[PDB]
Length: 329
Ligand SMILES: CC(C)[C@@H](NC(=O)[C@H](CS)NC(=O)CCC[C@H](N)C(=O)O)C(=O)O
Ligand SMILES: [Fe+3]
Image 1 (cartoon, protein in one colour):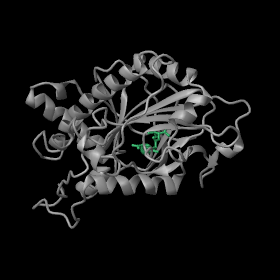
Image 2 (tube, rainbow, N blue to C red; image 1 turned 90 degrees about the vertical axis):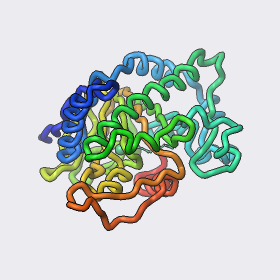
Image 3 (cartoon, protein in one colour; image 1 turned 180 degrees about the vertical axis):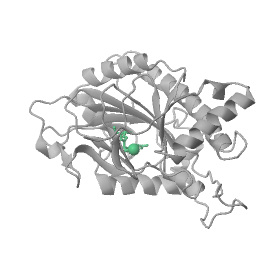
């Protein structure tokens, strides 16, 4: 069998308040989990995840093939050259099971200075017709801000955990310019499930998505109650239990770079499971020009032999690399 990964449940509610000592005790828990398997569940987070799941299901189960082409990213529809990140990511029956919808900062409007400058990684979201999907856009935009709020609180815990002031990361995570994204991923139940949509790991495990490190500062994930994730540890790949009441949190490779691998970006993969389920990540990305000077909390002077990297450079190249490694989603 496969061993269960150590993934503690951390009550993150003090990170929304002003009890500094209580916040330090949460930071310690974040530190411990980040130094161990690299994963934890954030609980007492204040977000209505049952309603998120319900609204997402209503969207996934009612969108039609016509609407998917009309919302498609450039990888599926050559007419949409501006849609690299935001839009619909189609399934390919018989070959690719997964499908999803990605959206960015709602403040990336046509008049936004980065949209006017045509800066890479910034795009204006595309949405289905309101009459076909009543309330969806409004729900989705509000969800972006609710999960942004949780992510800001989490970033205060990570900063304190690293011996910094609580705004160390959060000062670079702002509503007017964050490159953060929400992805509403549908993993379907299929009968027969196409073998071409099932990958096989070197250890024989059937997968839907191969091993990788995340392209993010941190990743804030809701998933249905169907076990699927595995994390590589010193004892090998271990199963991460599902918890559809909490948010699964881990660091991405920007955090590993900034901390000189004190907080590693854990390697993880997605097992193949023949079940209708949801995987709804929020990728906590900073602004395009955000630069955090690398440091090392294991070194007496805190210095590291790594060079500063702008978040926009990191992101554009990371997303392309992930597609080259693990395939177009
Ligand atoms: C592991 C889950 C987070 C999920 N995987 C994922 O979402 C995988 C690996 S973290 N992520 C990506 O492909 C990056 C999507 C980036 C997004 N188009 C954007 O422009 O910002 C899954 O369930 O497969
Ligand atoms: Fe990941």
